[PDB]
Amino acid sequence: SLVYEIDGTEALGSCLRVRPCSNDAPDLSKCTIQWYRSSSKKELISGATKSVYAPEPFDVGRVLHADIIYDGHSLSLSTVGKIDPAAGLGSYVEALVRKHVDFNVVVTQMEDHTSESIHLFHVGKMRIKLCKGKTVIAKEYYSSAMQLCGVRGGGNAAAQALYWQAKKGVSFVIAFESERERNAAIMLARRFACDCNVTLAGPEDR
Amino acid sequence: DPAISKDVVLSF
C-alpha cells in the first residue's frame, strides 16, 4: 500500500520532500523515486531520484511531481501549486547582467571533497571559471557540452548548491553562501550563455 | 553522473 505526500514550502529557496502517510507504506529507500516538472505534460528531472528535491530556476511557475514505485505499484504525487519565485531574484540578476562577476563558494564534489577553502566562481560574459587563489581549477567557454543546474539530491545545502559539468568527464558540485547567490549564478550563466547562442541547462533538460 | 545527486552538506 503506497501512501505518501510531498511536503515543504513551494518556493524557490527551499526543499521539498516525499513523506510517508501510512504505517504500512514501505520505506522510501526501497522505492524508486523520480521527480518531474510540468511543461500539459510533465518533463523528467534527470538525476532527481531521491526523496528530497530542491527547486532551481527552471522550476519556478511549474507544478512539481514525484512518481514513487515499489514492486509493480506506483503513485504519482504533485505539489499543491506552482513553485513560487524568490523575492528580489529577478532584480538582482538584472543588476549582475550589466557586468562582464564572482561568487565565493565551497567545492563539495570533483569524488567527495571536504574543504573549507573558499574558491571563486566567475560567471562571465563568455566563460565560466573556477579558481582557488591564483590557481585556476577549470575554465571553459559556454558550449553544448557544458551543463549547469541546481543539484538534484538531498542534504541541508541542496538549495544552495549547483552542479557544473565543465566539459565531458569534468564536473563539480559547488555550494554558495546563500540560496540567492546560488540561483543568481545559474540564471546569470544561462543568460550569458543564451547571448552566446548556447542553451545551458542540466542533463536532459527540455 | 552520481555527483548530480549526492547529498550536499555544509557546517562559510
Image (tube, coloured by chain):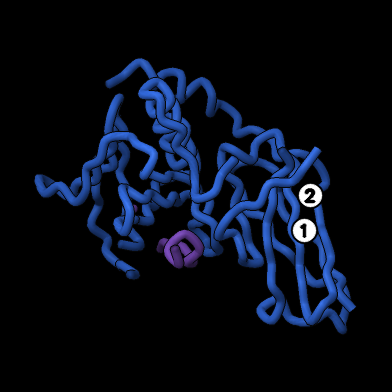
Chain colours: A blue, B purple
Seen at 49% across and 66% down, the residue is: B7
Q: Are marks 1 and 2 on the same chain?
A: yes
Q: Tell me the residue that label 2 is attached to.
A: A79
Query: Which residue is tagged 1?
Result: A6
For mark 2, name the chain: A
Callout 1, which amino acid? Ile
State whether residue A153 is above or below residue A27.
above
Answer yes or no: is residue B9 visible: no
**Looking at the picture, does residue A87 appear above or below residue A49?**
above
Q: In the image, A206: left or right of A160?
A: right
Question: Element under label 1?
Answer: strand
Pinpoint residue A107: horizontal percent, then vertical percent. 31, 57
- Residue A106 appears left or right of A67: left
Packing grade of label 1 (10 A; few <14, some 14-19, many >=20) is many
Q: Position of residue A41 (x, y in %)?
A: 77, 42
Asked if residue A25 is positioned above or below residue A177 in the image, the reply reads below
- Seen in the picture, residue A3 relative to A45 is either above or below; the reply is below
Q: Residue at x 41, y 30 (%)?
A: A198
| x then y, percent, for residue A109 | 35, 62
Q: Are marks 1 and 2 in contact (CB under 8 Å)?
A: yes
Image quarter hosting the C terminus of chain A: top right
Instruction: Measure the alpha-carbon separation of dots 1 and 2.
Output: 6 Å
